Image (cartoon, coloured by chain):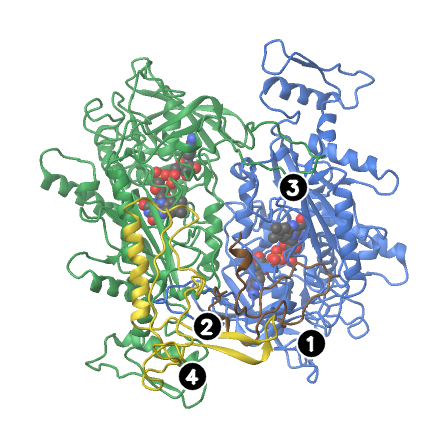
Chain colours: A green, B blue, C yellow, D brown
Amino acid sequence: KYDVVIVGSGPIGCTYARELVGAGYKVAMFDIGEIDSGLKIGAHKKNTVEYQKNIDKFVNVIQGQLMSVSVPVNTLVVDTLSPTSWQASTFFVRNGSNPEQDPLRNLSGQAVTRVVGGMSTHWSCATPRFDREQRPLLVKDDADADDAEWDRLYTKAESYFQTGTDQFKESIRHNLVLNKLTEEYKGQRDFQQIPLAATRRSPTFVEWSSANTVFDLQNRPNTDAPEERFNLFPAVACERVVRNALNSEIESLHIHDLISGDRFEIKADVYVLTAGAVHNTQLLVNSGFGQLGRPNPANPPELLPSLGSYITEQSLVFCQTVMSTELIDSVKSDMTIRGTPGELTYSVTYTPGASTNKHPDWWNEKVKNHMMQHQEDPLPIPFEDPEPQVTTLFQPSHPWHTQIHRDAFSYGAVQQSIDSRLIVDWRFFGRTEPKEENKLWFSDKITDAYNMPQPTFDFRFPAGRTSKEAEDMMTDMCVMSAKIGGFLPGSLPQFMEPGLVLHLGGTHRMGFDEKEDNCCVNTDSRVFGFKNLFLGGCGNIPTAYGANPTLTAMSLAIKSCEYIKQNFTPSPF
Amino acid sequence: KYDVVIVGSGPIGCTYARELVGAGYKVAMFDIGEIDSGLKIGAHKKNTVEYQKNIDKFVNVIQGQLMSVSVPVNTLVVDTLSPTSWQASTFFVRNGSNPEQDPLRNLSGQAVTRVVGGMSTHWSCATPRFDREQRPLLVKDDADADDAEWDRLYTKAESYFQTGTDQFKESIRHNLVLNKLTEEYKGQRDFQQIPLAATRRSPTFVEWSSANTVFDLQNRPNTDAPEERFNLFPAVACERVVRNALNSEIESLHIHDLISGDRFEIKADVYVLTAGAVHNTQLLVNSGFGQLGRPNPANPPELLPSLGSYITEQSLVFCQTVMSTELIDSVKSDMTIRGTPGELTYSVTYTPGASTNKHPDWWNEKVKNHMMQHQEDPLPIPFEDPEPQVTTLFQPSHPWHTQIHRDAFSYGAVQQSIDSRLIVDWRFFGRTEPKEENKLWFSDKITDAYNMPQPTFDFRFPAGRTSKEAEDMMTDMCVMSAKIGGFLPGSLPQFMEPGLVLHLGGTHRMGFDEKEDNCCVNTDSRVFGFKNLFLGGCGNIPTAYGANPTLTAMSLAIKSCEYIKQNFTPSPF
Amino acid sequence: VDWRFFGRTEPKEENKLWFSDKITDAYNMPQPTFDFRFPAGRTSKEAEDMMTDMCVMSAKIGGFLPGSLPQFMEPGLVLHLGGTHRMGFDEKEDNCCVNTDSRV
Amino acid sequence: NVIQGQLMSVSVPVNTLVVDTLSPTSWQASTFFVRNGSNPEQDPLRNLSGQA
Ligand SMILES: *Cc1cc2c(cc1C)nc1c(=O)[nH]c(=O)nc-1n2C[C@H](O)[C@H](O)[C@H](O)COP(=O)(O)OP(=O)(O)OC[C@H]1O[C@@H](n2cnc3c(N)ncnc32)[C@H](O)[C@@H]1O
Ligand SMILES: *Cc1cc2c(cc1C)nc1c(=O)[nH]c(=O)nc-1n2C[C@H](O)[C@H](O)[C@H](O)COP(=O)(O)OP(=O)(O)OC[C@H]1O[C@@H](n2cnc3c(N)ncnc32)[C@H](O)[C@@H]1O
């Protein structure tokens, strides 16, 4: 018996933990995955000395924990087997593929992560706010009020994640890019640092935020928390919440301890599902909400008819550039140079404080030192100079999010031929109109690796605005990236596979009114009809958004937690 | 002040910990890497429910922690940059390459792993014994005595690692392969299960051994060890051991706490280096043993002249096969089949205990169940059937180690087209003659990511036996693999990049006599001349070996630990 | 649909085709050798504005075909090499080889 | 294929690609010497590699 139970230990789950363990509830949290992030439970895997000295290698950590959601049956022809080897007569169901999935209407790139801390153990930590156009209303007919509430919620969310916008302010590459872009779009667009959940510790080490940052996930009571009550149970698959006959309350959470193989049931007053956009929906449909199986409109669901419909995922375009000759020369524009590199008479000098210096003394000092200490190196940028982290946020005239940066998650065998200091990544993210015909559904025959109903997508980017904007987005990336340099061969401008972007939303969408707004949960994230069932995550977001959704989902959880504290009484300790 | 200090937390380091913490020494161990394996410190990363349900993904975990030792300057031509982008006039030193390294005499595949538990957090857990031909002598002129000692040492080593040979005995694929090979080579070669440091927990879960298995790496005293004394310090780079003027004893270990940036010195009575074959040699050469810089025979080292010479690494050949039609039909040879799959009259039956049954009832039952429960599936092998794990050990008439199996570390984007149940991996490993001209050396100008002398290889597989055997090895793999099925397209027979195999040996080699045997340490693994300095690891092994070296290195550490216990007195507690 | 945009290149003295006095080609003639880079200045700016134009204009007709993404081709693949024996009125003033009748 | 069959490259620089998975028994280069009709005079970084 707990006061509250949480399914999932991602940062949205941890938002609920932090709020509710702190309010004095007896909390239990289960995760289907295991603790594997070192002694700080649920922390960012990027935060080791070894990874920030070899950041190129972290792509492999991310790849190692992205398990594809739905993989269609494979139809590749292999006709150079030896005559003696067993050979197929058909393309039969092999290697865990999903025979329900149409390869041409899939989110082939969608994947899930089963570890403690969830995807926040590997994420890129960008946490922009949504402007009105991207955000669901929290207050009808009172825009300035709706604005205040979101400002209040986001401000707390930024606290929990330790969101900041100046962690890269000392980077020559970052400023080089930022300044050129501002200059080029003078009074048509604004550029700034990407808001990032991150704390710099030194010039060569950044403590990337994660679930741990939100809530440290240590069992309580403990010494630094002697009146709080929290237990985390890793390696527990949660399978069904049990409805009462009235469909007014949840009575139990049914679980599978993966290590012993035993199943149990768990009672709480308050049930919170934060298993992610896909696995929330799976858990619910496994529990009698929505509809199991291939959509059949001639049998409507009894509960939550909009569950798994109106799903959104963002179009992503990508390239990388090599920094222009012009920009590179500009780095060292303040330097007077005498002699020829490599002789003892060679000299690179600047005049501090000189009025006609285009850069600050700190920048000049770095450049001078690098050029004198490394006279074999043909570039003015210091070896350890931190990466760019630039954005122009979504606007109506440019309704896409942009990151102009360096991401651990590169999409191909990485280059060694071109100097890393010249390379900038470009990622533009489009907003997707939510549509009823775009669905995530669960097979009533096929099951996944945990013996749950197999997830299946039926998705295409909507015709209309979504398609036009995506193409205008691609074109924008081409136009804007040219200002900084030419495309890097092998990273030419391209749309990424659908869902690789991992910003799936709308799978258990929020709204004021279940029928009128075609939704699943209300603005307290409570499941309509149910007193004690709450959903947290990107699944909640009902709007077409381009920016990274996590901070938004977090803000919604905070408001959800206000409701719980005002409506349920913690047990005595 | 400690009684003993150990550098490195790999399983060889942990062998020293286990022996010495258990003998009652005050032990400290430092690792340059960090704890990141979940709550069991130093354990196998493969031991999560999620990885053994998605084993294909573990390749990414291994890749994420293999940092290449020496990467030559890159000379690839990129001539499709945009005219505007900064373009090189030369192939200058970019992206951490090593300008000292000749690309044509490198071990390009050699890599290191900096995490707590070392490479044992990701290794494949094969732990064969070496036969006399592969093993260094521990006793001169008394072969039967030398045999007994090694039998004694290996038997303990197998205990520590939990080595077993029956963990896969229930696998249809494993037995299918094993039995065919035995049959084919009848009375010319013997096949058995690869000895593996592993404990099966269930039919779908194997607890893979690691450093943790050897020693749990928890700080002591603690409740289950209240009179023992051990501390582990992660994120500490050890840089130099300090010699006394006499070169008879080590006086301190010099360290760098990576998290605070501060340097300290550490006193112990006994210093143990187990940082791996490369990083032991680096630590030593950084400390005035051997020779820093490009080999210069006209300036001999003062100490340990053979340090970094005579290095061995094994030739590795690889392919994968698709199981023959014949073998696949044999699986179901005992089945009577009526009707046609997919109708309710279809029937697969066998007669238990029937004299003419070629397989045991358990095998038949599995096959019958699979064929009746999955009538859409064209193969008689059950979905969860464990992988093959077969070997014929090195002999004189076949002087190579062989693994006929399924390895998490596949060498290419993996297939989805061919059913996984049909696929077997083939890895044959050759022995390399140790030669003086084959060297690992450290630059006196270039430094690595931890500001230590940059490692550089000068290696070629020796002409003579080594080259002939390697080619006869390749041919053997072709001949033997054909017995089981044809090559899988995309995994055709090939030599792997030198050192990818990660069995590097001989870098601080063991022998009776420093000059006569051209070696660094004696049979107690003590550095010649030095009372209190010991080396552990594959670096010690002075012979040409084909089998996987870790259990051998462990046995040597055990004997090293006998010496220490008989020669140094633990402090009072 | 294929999209090919072709830029103009400023002629420069330092951009040269020359022939080895030691190395010979398959017909035992002096081996051809290039010393070429696209000129800084207008040539480089125009080439990049050209790439951008192709992106902007091609979008009007449809999205890029995967495997044929926008890219600069290897120098000279285009096979429009010019200026190697260039024409002009006056040999010294116009730095040239042949006159307007193409006579040397 | 007809076009490719009649375009002979004008100047091909000496090749520097590393092949380190030869069998130990096979003849192996110690240098990137002039092979297969390459032109040692040509700087790979200032070429018209596509000219034919
Ligand atoms: C992978 C990734 C994600 C990512 C990113 C780049 C990459 C490479 N960049 C980010 C960006 O810069 N910022 C942005 O806002 N998001 C970014 N993302 C996405 C981010 O990681 C996710 O949006 C965020 O993690 C969502 O958080 P939430 O807490 O909602 O979900 P979760 O992290 O997926 O964790 C859910 C967990 O629950 C578990 N689970 C799943 N099913 C069950 C069941 N049945 N029972 C018990 N537990 C369950 C998981 O194992 C998991 O930990
Ligand atoms: C990666 C791998 C290795 C492997 C294998 C397959 C793969 C993919 N398969 C194995 C096989 O089946 N069996 C076989 O016997 N070996 C197999 N291997 C090899 C195995 O992992 C290694 O042989 C074994 O781990 C060697 O153990 P040892 O304890 O000698 O070395 P280590 O694991 O590399 O750990 C050394 C550590 O010390 C650290 N370090 C390095 N430098 C320093 C300094 N300067 N200061 C402090 N610490 C240092 C490391 O971080 C490390 O943990």
Measured in 3D between alpha carbons, the distance from the residue under mark 3 to the one under mark 1, in whole angstroms, is: 57 Å
Between disc 3 and disc 2, the foreground one is 2
**Quadrant of ligand 2 in image:** bottom right
Measured in 3D between alpha carbons, the distance from the residue under mark 1 to the one under mark 2, in whole angstroms, is: 59 Å
For marks 3 and 1 on the same chain, the one whose residue lies earlier in the sequence: 1
Instruction: Quickly name the residue at label 3.
Output: B488
Q: Is residue A252 visible?
A: yes
Q: Position of residue A204 (x, y in %)?
A: 39, 64
Q: Toward the viewer: B366 or C10?
A: C10
In this view, B524 is above or below A15: below
Q: Amino acid at mark 3?
A: Leu
Q: Amino acid at mark 2?
A: Arg
Instruction: Note whether ligand 2 is within 8 Å of mark 1.
Output: no
Residue neighbourhood size for the residue with mark 1, other residues' Cα within 10 Å, grouped as few (<14), some (14–19), many (≥20): some
Measured in 3D between alpha carbons, the distance from the residue under mark 3 to the one under mark 2, in whole angstroms, is: 42 Å
For numbered disc 4, what is the local secondary structure?
loop
For numbered disc 3, what is the local secondary structure?
loop
In this view, B20 is above or below B187: below
Between disc 4 and disc 3, the foreground one is 3
Q: Residue at x 33, y 58 (%)?
A: C51
Between disc 3 and disc 1, the foreground one is 3
Instruction: Quickly name the residue at label 2.
Output: D46
Badge 2 sits on which subunit?
A: D
Measured in 3D between alpha carbons, the distance from the residue under mark 4 to the one under mark 1, in whole angstroms, is: 46 Å
Rendering quarter of residue C29: bottom right
Instruction: Quickly name the residue at label 4.
Output: A341
Q: Position of residue B393 (x, y in %)?
A: 79, 47
Q: Amino acid at mark 4?
A: Pro
Q: Residue at x 32, y 82 (%)?
A: C94
Q: Is residue A224 visible?
A: no
In this view, B323 is above or below A183: above
